[PDB]
Image (cartoon, coloured by chain):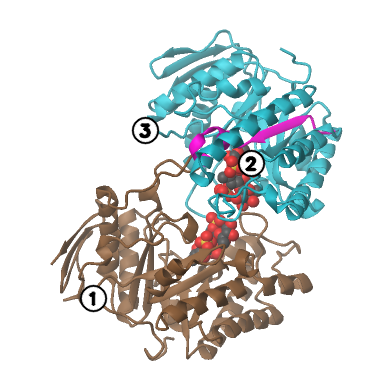
Chain colours: A brown, B cyan
Amino acid sequence: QNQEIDYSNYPEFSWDTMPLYMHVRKNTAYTDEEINYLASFPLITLEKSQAQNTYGSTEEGTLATASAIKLKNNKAKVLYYRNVVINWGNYKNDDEFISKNPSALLKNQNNELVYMPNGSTPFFDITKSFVQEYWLKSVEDMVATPNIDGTFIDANIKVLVPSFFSSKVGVNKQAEIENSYFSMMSRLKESLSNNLILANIIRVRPEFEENGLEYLGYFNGSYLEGFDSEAFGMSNAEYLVEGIEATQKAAQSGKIITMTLGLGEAIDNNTGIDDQREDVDLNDEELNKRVDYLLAIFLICAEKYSYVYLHDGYLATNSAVWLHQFDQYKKALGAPLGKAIKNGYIYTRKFENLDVWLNLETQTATLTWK
Amino acid sequence: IDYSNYPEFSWDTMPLYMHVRKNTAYTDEEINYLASFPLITLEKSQAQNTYGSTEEGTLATASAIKLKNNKAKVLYYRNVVINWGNYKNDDEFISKNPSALLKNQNNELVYMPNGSTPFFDITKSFVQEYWLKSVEDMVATPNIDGTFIDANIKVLVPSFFSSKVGVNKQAEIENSYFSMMSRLKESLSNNLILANIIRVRPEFEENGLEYLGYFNGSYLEGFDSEAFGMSNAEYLVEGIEATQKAAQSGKIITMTLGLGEAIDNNTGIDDQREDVDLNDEELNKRVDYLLAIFLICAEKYSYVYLHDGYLATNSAVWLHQFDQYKKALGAPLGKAIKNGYIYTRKFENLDVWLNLETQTATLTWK
Ligand SMILES: C[C@@H]1O[C@@H](O[C@H]2[C@H](OS(=O)(=O)O)[C@H](O[C@@H]3[C@H](O)[C@H](C)O[C@@H](O)[C@H]3OS(=O)(=O)O)O[C@@H](C)[C@H]2OS(=O)(=O)O)[C@@H](O)[C@H](O)[C@@H]1O
Ligand SMILES: C[C@@H]1O[C@@H](O[C@H]2[C@H](OS(=O)(=O)O)[C@H](O[C@@H]3[C@H](O)[C@H](C)O[C@@H](O)[C@H]3OS(=O)(=O)O)O[C@@H](C)[C@H]2OS(=O)(=O)O)[C@@H](O)[C@H](O)[C@@H]1O
């Protein structure tokens, strides 16, 4: 049920160099230097727990951060994170809503609250009309402010994979949650039609016939995580083949893609728990081979409005790549000269200033910059 | 050695340790389970969403455990430097005394990797006294037998705090830490003090034994998690040697070992978490291996916990007894013998075989 494509409210995009995405939180205000860094990205999602130890709440920390970004670069697009079912902390208005309205939280068929794996974070019962209205208004009100361009909707997949809630609250309640989810996304599709809606939705799933593409009709694009984390008995290569296919199709349909890929395992060095975390050599040859590989996966998929983030977590103060620009982000890229060519697990693609070769079996790639 | 305050111990079957938290009160069944262990540490965030605070949730839990088995020994967790949440008395103390928290030279708070949990500045006398009294007051209550002191190694590895507040402030933190542990050694001399202290470290020529004189025993973690460029096998060799020496000297050992991959199945994030078959052949091989490491080290007052995290409601082994915990074990008939990376040890009802290099063990039960 995709809408006719209208790019009026889309972020800036250029093929000149790597198109980059930022997805970030910090417990206190960003420094001036950090704001300048954020404002250099074309598309930024502000996560939950947004500077709440400076501004008292995520709502106020989001407003302050977005204002500061826009004053440095008013062309940067800023999205507000919102989880559609998990009642995470540090939203002052959510705390008040739940305090005053305990019936807003999700219960199992034995009338017990159900929780995330930490045993303490509960869920919104979005089947209840007043919860739907509270949640929708909270998103619409924040997006209507001058420095927020849209919203990042999270936990779509927890709604849509039936076992996630059916194992907690039963089969019928899962279907009711899903029905209400669709109602709520229909509401946002209309109310935010002059804004951006990005969702955490494309994902290799045995339950999804089209690996999330069938759910993109509500959204201007998808964020990607778990993209190289195989499951379901599939090999790493098999799993990436399906994710690449889905991402290519979505990107070629004009949807925004924000592909996140973790470097945490390539940076970890067995330090930082009971000793100082050893400074990572960001020029390390092996680390840069990993950057090449992950960027090759992205470039095999990318179209206009595709953006990449190679991250060490979304908390700014605990990320080894915070404030850093890899050399691969500065080199001339240029527009594609064709689609990727797939031969088994080997992919190639040509850009005006770059040739990409990717082997998913060996988890190696070459970026030959021209 | 004064054993008068030590826990019960028997070689009849595997000697077990429990180390646990839950956000709400334990059920009756869960209290009975806890009371079946000879030694239990109640972690931070102890039933605080039922009792309002870890302090009162600890008191309620300990009272219930002791009513079911008054011989069970119950320890109160206390972190010597990290200001973790859900202690109502700490929240009051820190709100009234913001200067109690550790700051750098710019008077900025420094934090754990989460960027939000700060540290006690134990270089300040009033912080030392608040902390010591908080431990002594809780241990003095009738259903608590002692304390589990955590984060010793964050004080004693100089880079942990020097990288945050400088080498000289770290040296002062260390000096104050030793003063505090000398104080506790005396005030808790009729109680138990267990510390997270034995650990393979390049900074520790004796891998933590040089600090064990303050305490009745050591808890072990990170025991099979190599670092510093060391092989897994040689890292375990050094930990085994430290643990053997401590146990043979009469110190309590509580060895925790994470079940690890064997109990992880790549589900539960966006889908239902699938049952891991607790009678699986491969899991049972991992249990055999981890218990073999323990048994190569164990002496009287050594206890083991093979875990899937310390949060009861998120652990696949909560309330579970592996078959290896029920079989007759019996007293050791000699110390372990080390031949390369292969260790053997005989007990009255068990022969242990262990190969660190392949991470394999054979338990031959009689
Ligand atoms: C602010 C922190 O929130 C919880 O941690 C989350 C974690 O959030 S973080 O901002 O990435 O650190 C992250 O949340 C996911 C993230 O939002 C991406 C974009 O989409 C989903 O994967 C999010 O997960 S979920 O909302 O569907 O669950 O990952 C979660 C699993 C949490 O991480 S966890 O490892 O801590 O469980 C808190 O748990 C943190 O303590 C912190 O408050
Ligand atoms: C209650 C939780 O506290 C923090 O989580 C800790 C975690 O605590 S837990 O009770 O095991 O879940 C654990 O703490 C360690 C544990 O106490 C052992 C016995 O000794 C040290 O290793 C403790 O760590 S530390 O105090 O020296 O840091 O491990 C920590 C690293 C934390 O786990 S973490 O992965 O979440 O960082 C909170 O972070 C939890 O959210 C929760 O509030």
Left or right of A257, for residue B5: right
Query: Viewer-nearest of labels 2 and 1?
Result: 2
Q: Are marks 2 and 1 on the same chain?
A: no
The answer to whether mark 1 is within 8 Å of ligand 1 is no
Relative depth, front residue between B151 and B230: B151
Q: Quadrant of ligand 1?
A: bottom right
Q: Check the image and report above or below for A54 versus B284.
A: below
Secondary structure of residue under mark 3: loop
Q: Amino acid at mark 3?
A: Gly
Query: Viewer-nearest of labels 2 and 3?
Result: 2
Left or right of A351, for residue B66: right
Q: Chain of mark 2?
A: B
Q: Quick check: is B150 in the magenta stretch?
A: yes
Residue A258 visible, this angle? yes
Residue B229's tag is 3
Q: Are marks 2 and 3 on the same chain?
A: yes
Relative depth, front residue between A332 and A307: A332
Residue A16's tag is 1
Q: Earlier in the sequence, mark 2 or mark 3?
A: 2
User: Magenta segment, which residues?
Assistant: B143-160
Percent coordinates x, y for residue B211 in the rendering = 59, 23
Residue A45's tag is none
Per the image, the residue denoted by label 2 is B81
Left or right of A186, for residue B124: right
